[PDB]
Image 1 (cartoon, rainbow, N blue to C red):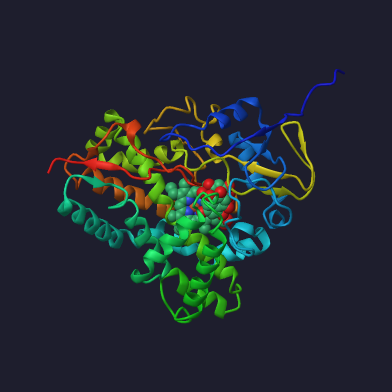
Image 2 (image 1 turned 90 degrees about the horizontal axis):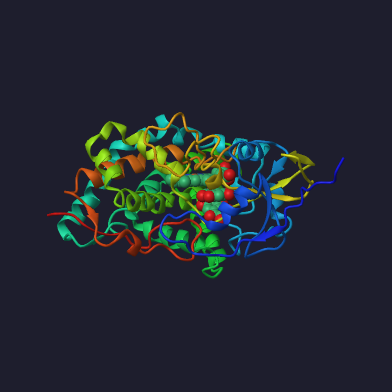
Length: 403
Ligand code: HEM
Ligand SMILES: O=C1C(O)=CC(=O)c2c(O)cc(O)cc21
Ligand SMILES: O=C1C(O)=CC(=O)c2c(O)cc(O)cc21
């Protein structure tokens, strides 16, 4: 019985700033190589496994045999020189503890929960768009709207005072500053970890609808510890700005394809489905994020993952799975059920998914029908994207309209 292979060599995945929303050439390679591959990233050390197919990604992210808690142990190979989550944040918690932590704020993030901030956010967005309309056609449709809106929405939902929004943005970008943008990221994490400790403890020891009040209440009832509450609050706060990057890519795409743009401009009722397809397609991040450690031996597509080995999943790769999404690279606003995974999978799935969709829907409504014929001020290829980041997106989005 011939001796075959299951030894894909370790392939280096250097830090590379990609153009616009173009797919990562290296990930394409890894995908076709096989369902299970091995990678080496800029920071940390080792060669972690990489899963890329839709079904296997769901398996790894939803199976108790793969944990996050142990990732803190050794120094797994990764993109960021530092680890983003705190030593007790949900990102580094497994089911037992992870479950009661997510349960503490779950009601604030369901479709029903986030719809409660819908109208409030709409007014907030109109104020930003109106201010832009007042300034003048030449505008940066990121600094004017895409950045300020998501920041205001997450701050209002978290219970962060408007006067502190600038601090949140400063710290978040230093932490997600592609991390290799220094490492000054650790001090920024600590400062943010101190801010939320104060907020949760200070004032949030009463009754409010905001998330920090909810967390403070849970801490007071001894349901979760401080630190657990702070760790979760910080990840929610930084994650809230993910909509800036993503919607930036969303509008760059739309403004690059007149066919797609007019259809959304003419058919408002198809916008929710269309936005979900865009979310599937847009390559949200550079490379991969946070791995999981095999807690025991597990076989994936004929490959034995040894206990202790690190394993990454690529949600971007899974969203381009030919088997699940026929003609993966094509943007089809109709799309069958299309269960992408841009918001992750398993216990760690994004708590902000519904909120992100709500924000994107409001942004599209305002940008397409509030601003008279908005359009890119330069060629799609001339739009500058962030070069040295974790979450991909425009550094600036030059636009004009018709006023
Ligand atoms: C279109 C915008 C967004 C995208 C594409 C996105 C995507 C993701 C992905 C891929 C993960 C990884 C799941 C894993 O660990 O395997 C994640 C986690 C997370 N996201 Fe988002 N996200 C978005 C917006 C948000 C927003 C607005 C918030 C704040 C409400 C948020 C909060 C979080 C948190 C707290 C986690 C960690 C969950 C955990 O480990 O339990 N996300 N997100
Ligand atoms: O763990 C990941 C991860 O592995 C990939 C991500 O994109 C991500 C993210 O966008 C936000 C997060 O809170 C966590 C992650
Ligand atoms: O981009 C990353 C990333 O590269 C690793 C992360 O762990 C992470 C995270 O825990 C939360 C985030 O919002 C983003 C990230």
